[PDB]
Image (cartoon, protein in one colour):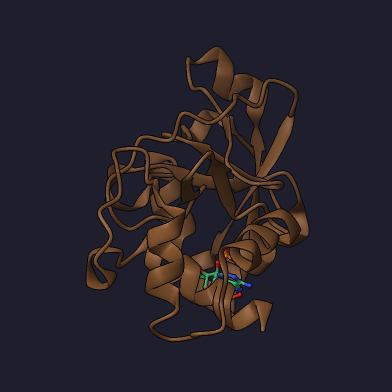
Length: 177
Ligand SMILES: [Cl-]
Ligand SMILES: [Cl-]
């Protein structure tokens, strides 16, 4: 199924490419032909055409293909430089978290995992569902994207709804939902 193969693709491209013999470049790209060979170790019926179809049909824009190169657009647990197109249009974004984090966030702002990027959403429901990954008592922060930009932060379009930014200062948190 598309779901099973996509879940494996996301694991390989975000978390464990070397386990499958793949060496991502600094931007997270691997050869799509080598990715097919890797995936076929688990699902031998997969084809390059199938992987390209998964990329084209993905509801979140999880993946990006350029020529012969494929990457995950977000969610890596290893260092990447993501030169995604800038979101210059959003006025408001959302960050899902858990209530226990408010104390720290209200003192320090939102910091990323591994000093990478903070993940934001254009959509409240997506932010809520993301926050549920860290606990049941979810709150969604409203982020003033214009004030982020005015402080010098570039907000990048990582997926259809996912946006990434280096840091969110407390001054740009405009509400809690
Ligand atoms: Cl909590
Ligand atoms: Cl996750």
